[PDB]
Length: 182
Length: 182
Ligand code: HEM
Ligand code: HEM
Ligand SMILES: O=N[O-]
Ligand SMILES: O=N[O-]
Image 1 (tube, each protein chain N blue to C red):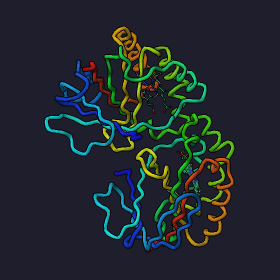
Image 2 (cartoon, each protein chain N blue to C red; image 1 turned 45 degrees about the vertical axis):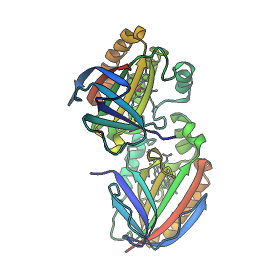
Image 3 (spheres, chains in turn purple, yellow; image 1 turned 90 degrees about the vertical axis):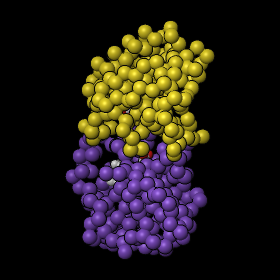
Image 4 (cartoon, each protein chain N blue to C red; image 1 turned 120 degrees about the vertical axis):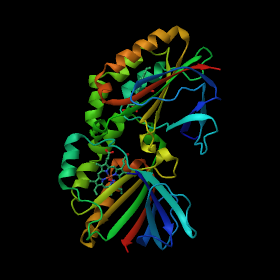
């Protein structure tokens, strides 16, 4: 039961890179494939362009009644139908991290409705949130979404809605890595 | 600016071990000294007995008005007179970590008054909170306190008040390493 996940862009992996969109700030080099490994990488293989890593952690903002709503409808990863995925690494500004817990919760849910908006796109979209600021990585979060092609248009709508939120005014680096399951 | 810290119990270090208290659950081996290093150490040196590590992280529970109170009084580390120190690794239960953010905040402060009680022992006591559950370590937190002998009795009071709090019903492993600055 290891909470560390690595994402290595390169020639090998379980996922074909469809495209990479460098939304904001320095991007990620285009590669053929992404290899996802659970655990800490011993040595990065040859012909790898980049390595991202993060860990699964405890809830930081969601309250019990939100967790109950998410749990009632959120799908599992690895659904046979979920052949599309998107890896989105995200970095938030130093202004964000300086803020107190009540100030960040108010932006996250009261002003931006992150959980309420996201719930609109379940059960179509499965997700996994990983943290990596505390590892000294270049991003603060590795977010992961997977879904069937039927939900691609919906997911693209969700992305536009989130980037218009107050919360995203604190995002200062973002890349979309679009993937297809091999 | 590396946020990782390592505490190596052994025969070298900047701190002499006065005593080790095996408060709850498996203890830590008694050693002569503790060595504190900033950064991640990959090879523990020979005739060291244990290594603890954690990182400095963002605020998880404190609200803005509590941060302002803490900042008004909390003392710096490495005060000339702060020749005593206590390193207290703590592990919380699986039931704690499964709880939602509002549930944990209400136990932490509304019921246990962690911050309000701690502020009573400032500015005598300087402190540093490190996290390590997300590193896969045996403990969840490494807490560090340092003060002059004048505040030894006050700090021992604080410990007894905290161990009787609702929050401590979720602690399942705890060790006190009492130190003296060399
Ligand atoms: C698909 C529906 C989604 C749902 C149901 C959802 C739900 C959530 C929840 C409940 C959290 C808080 C976890 C906690 O309390 O620690 C969270 C965090 C986060 N989500 Fe989402 N989310 C969705 C989509 C997205 C998308 C599309 C993105 C990025 C484009 C995203 C980026 C993030 C980030 C960066 C965080 C961490 C926030 C922080 O800790 O500051 N989420 N999400
Ligand atoms: C000396 C006065 C103290 C003050 C002013 C104080 C203040 C605080 C504050 C404000 C936090 C929350 C940090 C955040 O929001 O992320 C915290 C966390 C914590 N403190 Fe203290 N504290 C004190 C003493 C102690 C003592 C003596 C112990 C152990 C015996 C302790 C154990 C912890 C633990 C384990 C956490 C992490 C709680 C969690 O995230 O679940 N504290 N402290
Ligand atoms: O909900 N962001 O993984
Ligand atoms: O307040 N725990 O360092």
